[PDB]
Length: 104
Ligand code: HEC
Image 1 (tube, protein in one colour):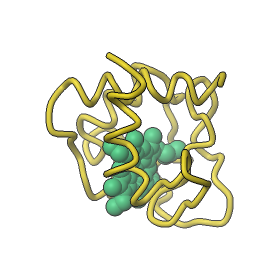
Image 2: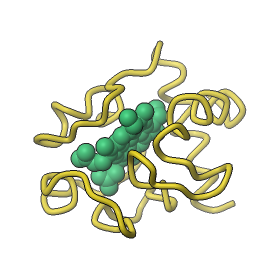
Image 3: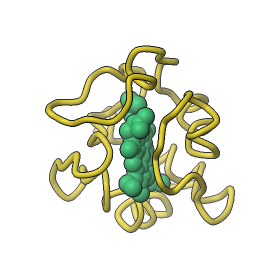
């Protein structure tokens, strides 16, 4: 649905690892420097896996939804300790939130 309905859940259980809207901090995942229509091997000084960066997929409304619904399965060895998001609303809410953070 909506940007409010996504930022409210991002700032709860994404910003805990990917601080961005509050101020950049890649403290347990890479801070989302837009991502939508960008690329994966894009983060500053952090460390994770080989898998995500080297293999890629282009981050977009498909791939990041497909990824957030199961990140461990979607890219081979991506740890990301959360792997789902309450209900399928918060999912599309996040997409439609972050889609502003790539043009606003
Ligand atoms: C800390 C335990 C995390 C939580 C909570 C969330 N994410 Fe995550 N994310 C985490 C890791 C360790 C990584 C690095 C990549 C790897 O392969 O391990 C990621 C990665 C992402 C990405 C992809 C970045 C890329 O590979 O280019 C995205 C788009 C992402 N994470 C988004 C995201 C959102 C929206 C979250 C809240 C629902 C979220 N993550 C939680 C660790 C953690």
